[PDB]
Figure 1 (cartoon, each protein chain N blue to C red):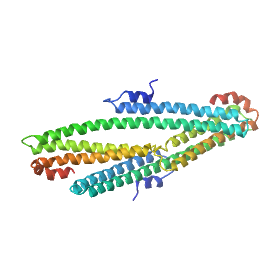
Figure 2: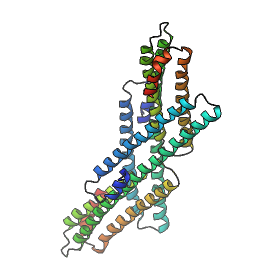
Figure 3: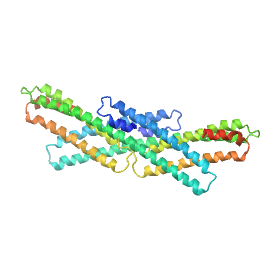
Figure 4: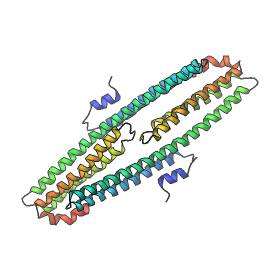
Length: 196
Length: 196
């Protein structure tokens, strides 16, 4: 019952996550090797048997396993891609809260009446950092559309490239925040471009 | 000059192989991360700059990097698939010699005038084993057509599924060899089916 994928998909948010993901891929792959060998041994028994038969039957037999194999190897390719895509999403969620928490701070510092320039930066590097870690991870996801099957792969790529463009704009929007507090801007500026 | 892929492709047959392959994937991936970050940092500088410009320019800029990224991530996906496919071939070569050497023996034993049944099996398990290890590895290759891009992926699958069918027939042909020496067949038979 609790299938490798079923389990993973049912125990989310996890703090240990990465473990689940590896335990997941490692456990699914194992089982796969099982069924795969079960079908391959099976295929032989079928050949040796039907051997003293017509080309029509021998051949037809081969067209059975050839197809049962293509059938499982596919479902298998999908279960994996199921794991990756879920995981990939759960990390995104994490990285996103981090992006959020750093910004709620950068805004916190930005608003202090005696705008301690030194602080703005402190809280901003943490924002720009997270944003960057997200930038990076979104890319990792893009590249993980390797098994590219339907147009789902092209659809995802578009969803990835799309969020990738947001990440940027939303940071530049966050950076435009300095203009409203035209002061800390100078003490921070030249330093800002350095991080960039 | 000696590109990660260039090097790998130029130092074959290797006995250490696996090392080359890992050193290869590890070194290509590293460099990739480099160019990728170079383009991502670059993209920002371009945004912050062109920011105080029209939607036409800002947007167009984004259409530059969006495309330069898709451009590199692809070439990158191809260089990798280049490594895998080469490696995958070189292993096949290896496993194939093993398939050969075991058969030259199984035939050697099969031909001894005083057909020592006990030996035929000894040399045959080694054949059927190799053949099986090949069976397995061909499958690993099939599943490694994950990045599926053009119809190259479908073309390869067909080449894989094709060799997969040969592996079988050629073993059953090798097994049919027992019939010509109708003797060792009985002492070996029931035992034969057990390995199967």
